Image (cartoon, rainbow over all chains, first blue to last red; front, side, top):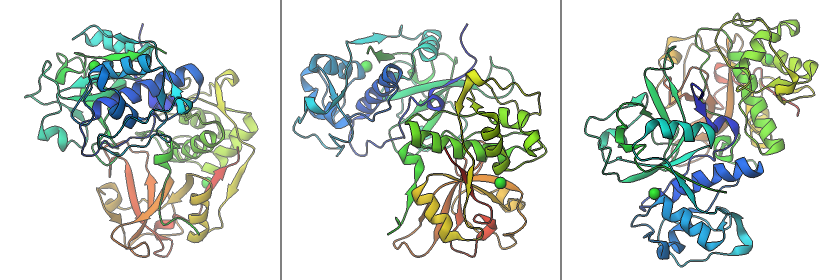
Length: 222
Length: 222
Ligand SMILES: [Cl-]
Ligand SMILES: [Cl-]
């Protein structure tokens, strides 16, 4: 069956933590983080991808740059657009700018995306175990999240339905010796390495889809 | 000529913070951290390596498993053995066990190791700026280290000669406005994320080889 724990950062699928700064673009960081892992699975090369390309160019697909967006609409843009530029060639400035997509600088493609069944944490565990990092949405609107530092995050006021922040599940695990209790999702944030635990947070797992991590998960098909 | 600050975590050289638990294997975590950084430099792939393989198998080279050892004897074993297994293939259980090395699971190799000039922090600063993370030993035998939480660690009773703990220097920097004062070494520990500053500590730099950080530094040759 599935592994008791998974951590794709230990296999080379994940880039160093980034910082979206004062721009509502976490959906773009979540999408590039999922496509970075799928392109690494496919080619063996880890290449940081451009959030700014997504902020500036995916309005036609329904995103609104620094005003918000959705990872599935980003993967739809990369498919429709035929590519996505590297972080190095199309740098992040955290403000809406003119679309400067350059095909010659493209280092990634996708044909669409796969959705995890909504609200199903075991479907998400299977996707994380067999595919690589997965884009998810969560309810991050709490000071307990803003000031998180360590341990398993559990917020009684969390919603599993009304979400406001895109993040990336890079694995799952458990504390202690028993693999079926005190479980958690390993989640990469885009608030810089200085936030949380080196930029990451353990979110309580199999506790009624806490903070909505399994409500709107998806990954690009490469 | 040398950079005023360096942080290899930003360039993809460093795996997540690990936890040796109740086993005197810090020398093994220091060694795998250095070899993870040199293999990434060589291949572009960051892959977690097996501390358990070093604990269980390097007795011939003079290591003593959970009862202590040396990063240099670890690099010697990888050279004599012709390989070192991935953590994924050879998981860590924090106890001394029978060697289970399998060459088919090897993901790393080295031809020996290089020693930094002893006691010379400027030689250590140069190796850190030009090679990547460096294995070092330090005097961690004070309660102030066990309870460290943030800031620049300075322990008046520290020794630079009698060292008892292997750690990994991943960079260096300074607090405040100018580069010449309040300098520190950026150190990755192996006591899990919950210890210290999310598993890391800043040790005073250019304060007379504080805690012995430059006394016994080295890195594998890949
Ligand atoms: Cl979405
Ligand atoms: Cl040593």
